[PDB]
Image (tube, chains in turn brown, blue):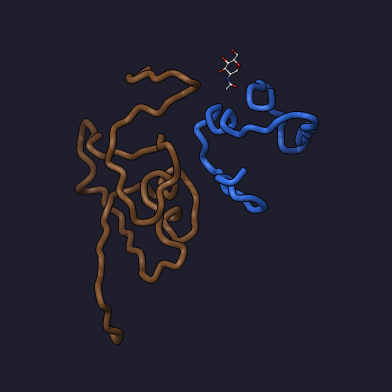
Length: 97
Length: 48
Ligand SMILES: *[C@@H]1O[C@H](CO)[C@@H](O)[C@H](O)[C@H]1NC(C)=O
């Protein structure tokens, strides 16, 4: 409460339990590499509280999404909304399977 | 041949294979498994 900040950014996203421990400056994993990477010299703080009442229901819910397939790592504080099938081998294949 | 094995030994007897006289491309290593922990100490995995 005793410091004056030039700007504050609030990035929010639902994520699984272990990837909460994944979220930290200088880390590794499918989320810290392809979905969200924090800067190594991060000046900020993280918040995580459980929510089983708004992200759950009978018969289930599958609205949420995450990426494990990207051409390269995510440089810090970049968003990569794109649906491109990851190439395997040498095929220009565009589809699932 | 190290990633395509079927009998990865138990931790009490850690199988130790030696890799010599070959060209190391780790793209096959990336492709051949949906990694869970690529955490590396001695080298940066991108610069491998
Ligand atoms: C193991 O080898 C077979 C040989 O055709 C290959 O098709 C398969 O993808 C390999 N799988 C793993 C898990 O190593």
